[PDB]
Each structure stands twice: as C-alpha cells, then as structure tokens.
Length: 209
Length: 209
Image (cartoon, rainbow over the protein chains, first blue to last red):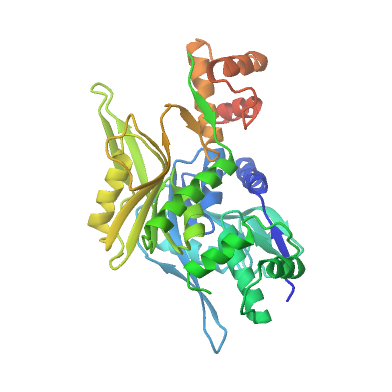
C-alpha cells in the first residue's frame, strides 16, 4: 500500500557527490583508479572523478539474486574479467549501501582480480539500520529509512512503483487520473519526474502491461 | 584568447539523453548490453539504460594520444579485457563525437573482443564538420562548433579554461576579480558552475599552480 519515497534531484546528487569527494580530499587518499559498481555507481563515480581529478574509471556489473524458497540473498559479479591495477590506489563507488553486500563483494573481487596497492569504498548514502559492513567513505548517513529515487532511475523506479499499484488494485482498464491519485496516496508524489502517462506507454512497450 | 563555451545543464543532459533513447525505441533496436566509453559515456549510458530498461552496463577506458612532432592523433584502449557478449545486441555510448575515432575504435574493439550479435553506436552530440565516421544514433547534430561543458566536467573544464588564461598571462599568479573578468571576456561566462575561487584552491592542491 504505502511506501516512503523521496525523489532525489540532480542538484542533490551534485551536493552529495561533492560532499563525498571532499571527505576523500580531506583524508588525503590518493585515488588513481575508480571502480564503479554498475549500474548504481556509474554516475557518482564520474562526478567524484571530476572533483578529485581521476582519469581512470572502470566498472563491474553486480547482480542481486534471491533464492525463492529460502529467501536467501546473493550478490554476484556478471561478465567477470581482470586487469592489472597493481601500484594503484583504487576507490570503489556505489550509489547507496545497506547490508553492504555489494561493496563487500566488489572489494573482495577487486583485491583478488585487479590486485591494487590499496582499496577503499564509498557511497553517496549509507543506511545505518541494515548496515552490516560499512563503507570507508560516504556523503550522508540515512536515519529515516526511505525509498530513494535517483535521477538515473526515474523511469525504472516509477515503472515498478506503478506496477505495485496495478498489482494490488487489480486495475483492468487503467485510468490515468485514478493512477495519479493512487500514486499521490501510496507514495506522496503529486508531480512524478516522468509523467505517469509516459510511464504507462512504456510499460506497454515492455509487455509489462 | 577567446573560446566559444556553452555550459550544459543537467536538464539539458536529461533532454538529450531522453531524445537519444527515443530514437533507439523508434528504430526498434533491442539493446541487451550497453558499453559505455569511459569517462565521457558513463553518465549518458546510465540515463539511456533507464529509459530503455537495460540492466547490463559495461565500460571501456579510452585514452587519446597526440604525437608531439607529427601532431598525429591516436585513441587507445587502456586496461583491455574481454568478456563473452555473444547472442547480445550491444549499444556503445559516448558523450560527444567529432572525428569519430573513439566510437570507430570502440566498435572495432567490441566486435573482436566481446563478439556480440550486433553493435550500434550513439552519442548525445555529433559535430558534422569534424565528422569522419558517423554514429548510428545521436540526440543532436551540432552545426555551430563550440566547447560544450558537460555537468560531469565542470571542475576539469573550468580548471583547463582558467589555465589557458593563466598561461597567456605569463605569470600564473592572479587576482580573483581579474580572473572573473578574463573569464567573462574569453568565454562569456559570468557565473561559472563552480566558483573560480574553488577552482584556484584545487589547481593549487593539484600542483598546477
């Protein structure tokens, strides 16, 4: 029914990214290479590279799997590969961390497969509740758990949010004005970044409806 | 002394990215994997993935080299590696193309090293003048050659633009208020995204001055 949803703007992304970079400047960690976790860490990685002056950005695709019956969570590196990053200080970046599985995994992967001089980890945001393993750097500690909608996820996030509504309410003949109401009601968003008509058009194109 | 400089905002990036994606929707190219050319294509790749619903994003670091005496230009893949992308339709993305060397190179590299089912190329912008090889997809053809300052390059671009000023001004020491004037004068920007004092502080940190 109701989900806590914060729409993050580009400006906030800039603020958070800049704040994260500034912590790294202050700690005097000399980053040679940034490894972005795809897809979440791509944008933050690029912005942080701009502020710090990093030229070498790489990325690793990380999948998140759940086992149906046991509800066991497993993160996995898709399209694994290796390169020689020895003599380098590596910074690993992702958008947001909770259980810390992704960054834990990426850190491990990077140590064994790229063998850098040193690895550190960073995210724009970290949720302290779910926090299992905690990132070396972060822009902002989240206290109030929420669903953060990032500007590089507006489409995907709105699609899923609209699907949760379509599934619960058993809507057959979708009404746009009805949807906007359900949306404002479940999520608190009266003006979604992508207009909900575009979202439906695209859900159709994708054979979701 | 004077350079044509357009400051690109986040909103414009969104427009261009969305417009590019829409051409791909319209052409009904079924993208399985996006390969972003680092560093330029990372942000566009992620936004395009959101609009199209691509989950698999990889990236390749491309360097640009010039031979001092001959002034010969050469793009090169740094930290090369391979993965198996067979049975996939790949889309290669970069921010902007002119001579088309990077996309030419990446296309080649991807064909030989990832061996996808098919490859196509895309950029936000393409300069028709310099255009040697032209991208399969693009948001916008540039007619008036300019220096486009993307939001993920605000620091790096301002640093270089300020350096061009410090160099012609044979000293490299300079007064903040004369810098702002030189900047407005050479480039037409009265309010740079990053304030020019921050830029000097960082040029120092970087031992550029």
